[PDB]
Image 1 (cartoon, each protein chain N blue to C red):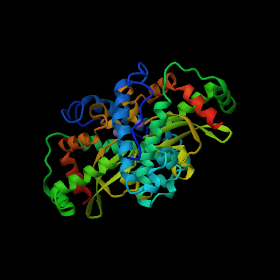
Image 2: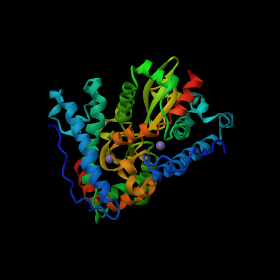
Image 3: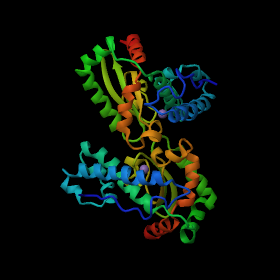
Length: 206
Length: 206
Ligand SMILES: [Mn+2]
Ligand SMILES: [Mn+2]
């Protein structure tokens, strides 16, 4: 009830040849759906939380009943992260404008940022996410475990900041095409990171 | 150096039709190799710890420095776990003998244990392992995150006990064949869990 699997900005094959259509379909119809379903299941008993946007719910995980924290952290996190991820994917964009300049300001150069992002994405051990976040006035690359989001805050996720964009580095995001070669997937991410959406999120939050 | 990739006890396709040969090859030659490589790299500056069997090293994670604990927990963990995993996989075995009796004693029935194992393997959120462990004289089903091992102890891994067998539920262990259908993979594991080795391990620290 509370959450719905969001309508994608695109068909499953829209990120070809970079992100494989089989994975995008499963990622949405199976993995994301499951996060929505399991978050919804957990929120049935929590009407005072079920109304929150998922992105707000995950900032309030410390307010949930103890026995709800993990399931919603994982599944509302998964829902939030995947919802962001899809909107954060698009071919044909160019990093530009204020976001490019902020990246250049905060990382020294786009290449420095990319290397830092790639390093975070590659070094995330196990499942998780690499993020470009905005922490007040400064962009940062952080990473989170599993479906943790920086929106969850430091205490829960070990990261914080508003996610400008993120890269799913769960193996389900890349295994079918890339298998263990997560760096290749990370490189491909640069071809599909939706800088227009990242720029819009930066514009909203900067 | 410190660690080597062990030979598989079997050919890449020896677990077919249950576990796919492609995954077995990548899982062994890439993922396990990488754990070996990265554990070896981290041990290069740790002479005090570099000569230890991997299963002993992962019991001493709390003794290494902080810039080494995680890398070795993850990679020596991965090496320990995959080493066990390969030996713990074999077609044609039959659960029997003291191990079957102890499973029946501690879980009520083989099916009860299998259901509890499957639950633990399915509910492991993110990457990790499901374990049959022996805790003193009681078999238990536990799961660990990432490449944590029960051998690592409760503080680090959230689990303890002597692993009798384990199931890798990292998505790289099953995604190529099963994609998101980890329960199908978990069910297939019953066809390839090496009960002989599980029995041998059970007899070894019973
Ligand atoms: Mn995902
Ligand atoms: Mn594995």
